[PDB]
Image (cartoon, rainbow over the protein chains, first blue to last red):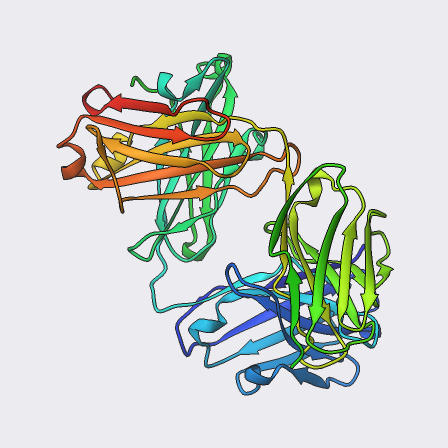
Amino acid sequence: EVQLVESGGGLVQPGGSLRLSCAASGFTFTDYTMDWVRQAPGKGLEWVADVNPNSGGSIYNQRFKGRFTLSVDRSKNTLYLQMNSLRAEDTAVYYCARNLGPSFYFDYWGQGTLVTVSSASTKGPSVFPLAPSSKSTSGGTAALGCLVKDYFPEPVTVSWNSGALTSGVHTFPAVLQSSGLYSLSSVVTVPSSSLGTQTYICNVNHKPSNTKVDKKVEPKSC
Amino acid sequence: DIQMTQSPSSLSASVGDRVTITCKASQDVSIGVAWYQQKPGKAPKLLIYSASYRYTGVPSRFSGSGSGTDFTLTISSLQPEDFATYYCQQYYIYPYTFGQGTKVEIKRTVAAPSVFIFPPSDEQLKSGTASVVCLLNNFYPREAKVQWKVDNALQSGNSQESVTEQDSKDSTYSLSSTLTLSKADYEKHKVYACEVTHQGLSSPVTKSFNRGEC
């Protein structure tokens, strides 16, 4: 199978530096050229640069010349995007993509890696229970969840019962509060008959702050 | 440089409907156009290249046409999983520009939201703040209004909401609205309620609780 895995994204201050990596596999790495395409939050797509893993020659998009440098290790099937003098406008998800034909359309893209350029400090989230009660019960269905509040930067991952519970789960897109910190809720609907019989724990992981929290959500009187 | 302009910016179509999206190039680009599909939280996927070539493994319902300055992407029979943003791109002339994208949503039968409310936890209170959450679950259309009331007073500027991306299996949406107050302010009031209005509700629905009892 074909796969492109990016890594290296994260938080960096304006004028800071970062190196993104793209590990390729499942095809003759040197038979194609590789590119980076980015997408700023809620915006469109913007081509960044292309590099030929055989000659090391690279083509860049105008405004990135001077602060972005492409390189490749033809011994690990990896591509690198070195970034310096980062600007707030560089905040985006950077995708690695394979360029098959001579033309510039990409047939395979990695999942991307998030780069956040901000002077704000990293902060782990508080995790509060969204306790189920008669107020969150509708017949045979009851809702419960966890509020993941005041963290930075994105993203946080939330699972239920260590991934054992997936159906009925809704982890909402984070919202940026006035304080400059993110907040989101993850909820799950379950049959009412399972409330007092099943244990519900939300597992929150905020890699940027290297924080992992588990929170048991128990029914309450309300 | 060459600009790629798509239309419409967004559209809603029913499952089984034929959908047509257009892309206009600011100048002749012969057949050097590609189309991509990008689902929420996923990386784009190549659908069409050379304007009319469906890429290997792409579902047959996807096809592209056009040449010169007018291009079109057609979904012969829209499927629930097709909810996504579709982008065109011209790739012969540097800097290989993409269109702004067209958001495609699935129009389904109206479904009223189930409404749930959650009082702030005692844990958060000892943190100095109180967040009250109102959940609107599995509804359609996306348009819904949530109004917070504290002791019957309409709130403004102290709440935020988030909507999930359209469900790829049943085409519904869910929404969370969070009202946040300092512990001091929260304890100065009794009744907390969220009123929900939606096309599927014949009359607004209100969920509430009394602070002292929760």
